[PDB]
Amino acid sequence: MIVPVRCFSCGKVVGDKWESYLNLLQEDELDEGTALSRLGLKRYCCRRMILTHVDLIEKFLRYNPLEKR
Amino acid sequence: AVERKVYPSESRQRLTSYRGKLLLKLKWSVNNGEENLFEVRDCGGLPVMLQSNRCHL
Amino acid sequence: LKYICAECSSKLSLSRTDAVRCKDCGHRILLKARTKRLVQFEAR
Ligand SMILES: [Zn+2]
Ligand SMILES: [Zn+2]
Image (cartoon, rainbow over the protein chains, first blue to last red):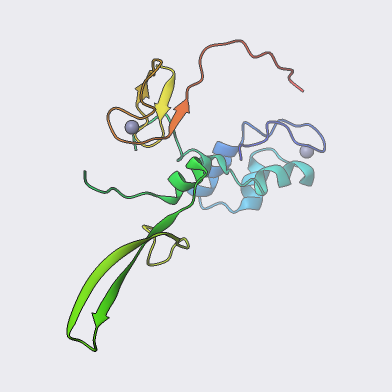
Protein backbone atom coordinates (compact mmCIF):
# COMPACT_ATOMS: atom_id res chain seq x y z
CA MET A 1 0.00 0.00 0.00
CA ILE A 2 2.27 2.75 1.34
CA VAL A 3 6.04 2.38 1.67
CA PRO A 4 7.07 0.80 5.00
CA VAL A 5 8.90 3.37 7.10
CA ARG A 6 11.30 0.81 8.63
CA CYS A 7 12.75 -2.44 7.32
CA PHE A 8 11.22 -5.45 9.05
CA SER A 9 14.32 -7.58 9.64
CA CYS A 10 16.80 -4.96 10.87
CA GLY A 11 15.03 -1.63 11.29
CA LYS A 12 16.85 0.62 8.85
CA VAL A 13 14.54 3.44 7.77
CA VAL A 14 13.61 2.71 4.15
CA GLY A 15 10.42 4.78 4.09
CA ASP A 16 12.23 7.90 2.89
CA LYS A 17 13.69 6.13 -0.14
CA TRP A 18 10.70 5.05 -2.27
CA GLU A 19 10.36 8.32 -4.20
CA SER A 20 14.12 8.58 -4.73
CA TYR A 21 14.15 4.95 -5.90
CA LEU A 22 11.45 5.71 -8.45
CA ASN A 23 13.39 8.78 -9.59
CA LEU A 24 16.58 6.73 -9.98
CA LEU A 25 14.67 4.18 -12.05
CA GLN A 26 12.92 6.82 -14.17
CA GLU A 27 15.40 9.62 -14.89
CA ASP A 28 18.56 7.53 -14.98
CA GLU A 29 18.51 4.18 -16.73
CA LEU A 30 19.60 2.47 -13.51
CA ASP A 31 18.39 -1.05 -12.88
CA GLU A 32 16.94 -2.06 -9.53
CA GLY A 33 20.18 -3.48 -8.15
CA THR A 34 22.27 -0.40 -8.92
CA ALA A 35 19.52 1.93 -7.67
CA LEU A 36 19.20 0.03 -4.39
CA SER A 37 22.98 0.09 -3.96
CA ARG A 38 23.15 3.84 -4.58
CA LEU A 39 20.31 4.46 -2.13
CA GLY A 40 22.45 2.93 0.63
CA LEU A 41 20.59 -0.38 1.05
CA LYS A 42 23.32 -2.97 1.63
CA ARG A 43 21.67 -5.93 3.37
CA TYR A 44 19.27 -7.90 1.20
CA CYS A 45 16.74 -7.58 4.03
CA CYS A 46 16.76 -3.83 3.36
CA ARG A 47 16.94 -4.29 -0.40
CA ARG A 48 13.77 -6.41 -0.57
CA MET A 49 11.66 -3.77 1.21
CA ILE A 50 12.12 -1.22 -1.58
CA LEU A 51 12.62 -3.74 -4.40
CA THR A 52 9.28 -5.47 -3.81
CA HIS A 53 7.05 -2.63 -2.61
CA VAL A 54 3.83 -2.46 -4.61
CA ASP A 55 2.54 0.99 -3.59
CA LEU A 56 -1.17 0.17 -3.81
CA ILE A 57 -2.17 3.48 -2.22
CA GLU A 58 -1.99 5.08 -5.67
CA LYS A 59 -4.75 2.74 -6.83
CA PHE A 60 -6.60 3.26 -3.53
CA LEU A 61 -6.56 7.04 -3.93
CA ARG A 62 -8.69 7.28 -7.08
CA TYR A 63 -11.85 6.43 -5.09
CA ASN A 64 -12.20 9.79 -3.36
CA PRO A 65 -15.63 10.31 -1.73
CA LEU A 66 -14.93 13.97 -0.86
CA GLU A 67 -14.38 15.20 -4.43
CA LYS A 68 -16.71 15.63 -7.39
CA ARG A 69 -15.66 13.15 -10.07
CA ALA B 1 -39.88 11.68 -14.72
CA VAL B 2 -37.07 10.28 -16.88
CA GLU B 3 -35.43 6.98 -15.98
CA ARG B 4 -31.77 7.15 -14.95
CA LYS B 5 -29.05 4.51 -14.93
CA VAL B 6 -28.45 2.46 -11.78
CA TYR B 7 -24.96 1.07 -11.29
CA PRO B 8 -23.73 -2.04 -9.45
CA SER B 9 -21.93 0.24 -7.00
CA GLU B 10 -25.36 1.63 -6.11
CA SER B 11 -26.77 -1.90 -5.91
CA ARG B 12 -24.03 -3.00 -3.49
CA GLN B 13 -24.34 0.15 -1.38
CA ARG B 14 -28.14 -0.13 -1.13
CA LEU B 15 -27.84 -3.82 -0.18
CA THR B 16 -30.39 -4.57 -2.90
CA SER B 17 -30.30 -6.53 -6.13
CA TYR B 18 -28.98 -5.31 -9.49
CA ARG B 19 -31.86 -6.35 -11.74
CA GLY B 20 -33.16 -5.15 -15.09
CA LYS B 21 -36.73 -5.11 -16.34
CA LEU B 22 -38.17 -8.10 -18.20
CA LEU B 23 -40.74 -7.39 -20.92
CA LEU B 24 -42.78 -10.04 -22.74
CA LYS B 25 -45.35 -9.19 -25.41
CA LEU B 26 -48.26 -11.59 -25.00
CA LYS B 27 -50.25 -12.63 -28.06
CA TRP B 28 -53.90 -12.82 -26.94
CA SER B 29 -55.05 -14.55 -30.10
CA VAL B 30 -58.66 -15.74 -30.33
CA ASN B 31 -60.20 -18.13 -32.87
CA ASN B 32 -57.07 -18.86 -34.93
CA GLY B 33 -56.26 -15.26 -35.81
CA GLU B 34 -59.64 -13.56 -36.11
CA GLU B 35 -58.20 -10.78 -33.93
CA ASN B 36 -55.00 -10.52 -31.90
CA LEU B 37 -54.71 -8.41 -28.74
CA PHE B 38 -50.98 -7.80 -28.33
CA GLU B 39 -49.67 -6.37 -25.06
CA VAL B 40 -46.22 -5.98 -23.56
CA ARG B 41 -45.91 -6.36 -19.81
CA ASP B 42 -43.38 -5.90 -17.03
CA CYS B 43 -42.46 -9.17 -15.30
CA GLY B 44 -40.63 -7.93 -12.23
CA GLY B 45 -36.91 -7.40 -11.93
CA LEU B 46 -34.68 -9.91 -13.71
CA PRO B 47 -31.20 -9.98 -12.11
CA VAL B 48 -28.41 -9.45 -14.63
CA MET B 49 -24.76 -10.46 -14.41
CA LEU B 50 -22.03 -7.84 -14.33
CA GLN B 51 -20.09 -6.84 -17.46
CA SER B 52 -22.77 -8.43 -19.65
CA ASN B 53 -24.60 -6.73 -22.50
CA ARG B 54 -27.46 -6.08 -20.04
CA CYS B 55 -25.13 -4.13 -17.73
CA HIS B 56 -24.06 -0.50 -17.97
CA LEU B 57 -20.40 -1.58 -17.56
CA LEU C 1 -23.50 19.52 6.83
CA LYS C 2 -23.18 16.07 8.39
CA TYR C 3 -23.82 13.99 5.25
CA ILE C 4 -22.22 13.56 1.84
CA CYS C 5 -23.97 12.35 -1.29
CA ALA C 6 -22.62 9.06 -2.58
CA GLU C 7 -22.74 10.06 -6.25
CA CYS C 8 -22.02 13.81 -6.48
CA SER C 9 -20.12 14.12 -3.16
CA SER C 10 -21.93 17.31 -2.14
CA LYS C 11 -22.24 18.18 1.54
CA LEU C 12 -25.82 18.32 2.78
CA SER C 13 -27.53 18.48 6.18
CA LEU C 14 -30.76 16.61 6.92
CA SER C 15 -33.31 17.95 9.38
CA ARG C 16 -35.96 15.80 11.02
CA THR C 17 -38.99 14.69 8.97
CA ASP C 18 -36.97 15.34 5.82
CA ALA C 19 -36.40 13.41 2.62
CA VAL C 20 -33.40 11.06 2.69
CA ARG C 21 -32.03 12.14 -0.68
CA CYS C 22 -29.53 14.50 -2.23
CA LYS C 23 -30.62 17.96 -3.34
CA ASP C 24 -28.29 18.67 -6.27
CA CYS C 25 -29.06 15.23 -7.72
CA GLY C 26 -31.48 12.42 -6.97
CA HIS C 27 -29.30 9.84 -5.24
CA ARG C 28 -30.81 7.96 -2.30
CA ILE C 29 -27.48 6.92 -0.71
CA LEU C 30 -25.96 9.39 1.76
CA LEU C 31 -22.56 8.88 3.37
CA LYS C 32 -22.08 10.20 6.89
CA ALA C 33 -19.24 12.68 7.28
CA ARG C 34 -16.41 12.51 9.80
CA THR C 35 -16.31 15.45 12.22
CA LYS C 36 -13.56 16.73 14.54
CA ARG C 37 -13.50 14.48 17.60
CA LEU C 38 -10.58 13.11 19.60
CA VAL C 39 -9.70 9.48 18.79
CA GLN C 40 -6.82 8.38 21.02
CA PHE C 41 -4.52 5.64 19.73
CA GLU C 42 -1.22 3.93 20.47
CA ALA C 43 1.72 4.08 18.06
CA ARG C 44 2.20 0.32 18.22
ZN1 LIG D 1 16.97 -4.30 6.69
ZN1 LIG E 1 -25.91 14.18 -4.91
